[PDB]
Length: 117
Length: 127
Image (cartoon, rainbow over all chains, first blue to last red):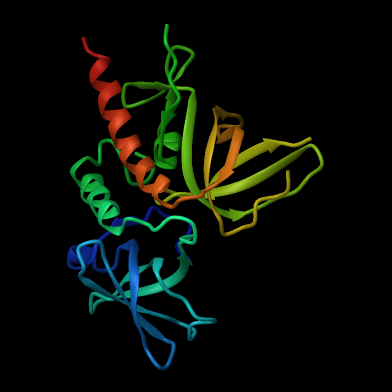
């Protein structure tokens, strides 16, 4: 913990609020990188913003679609413990579609369960 | 009777239990399955290669691939087709196909296909 041993919930930014302190999975487009390298902004499939906080300043540069894994802060930002740049080079990732999937994941937890049930 | 290749989340696999000689999550019999996750750790051996594959849904799972190309680099996304087997009360997947994800959209497709197949088959099983 290091959260790789727990279920993590795929959310959009619309849901941050309903997820304080829970482990989550935020997929978004890189909007801004803070000068310090310690914080950055991703916009979800509905074009809304989530703030990603870091422990160590960003190691190298990132952009495009990033998938962040972290705990939702008291301030409803995300303390990130790892991220992944999405292989985009041959086909662009439809961020809007993914957003529908997220919604559907939450209308149907009996069919996309979270953790051993 | 008929045995489809059911798309799944790892949380579904770890939750499936044995019921009359076949694995079952919800009331969907499963055997052949595809998952899509992210290689968190490779493990080389000459016979077999063991991966730790993580989607969102639970702790990463073991995926064994029996060798005979190269070891897929930790960090990459992959689709996996295989058989769900449990040995020492521990579920693992026996992969026939492990293919680095080309178009990250396939990944969304999967989330959609899982929720869909599971919804359809569980309905079809009544009745």
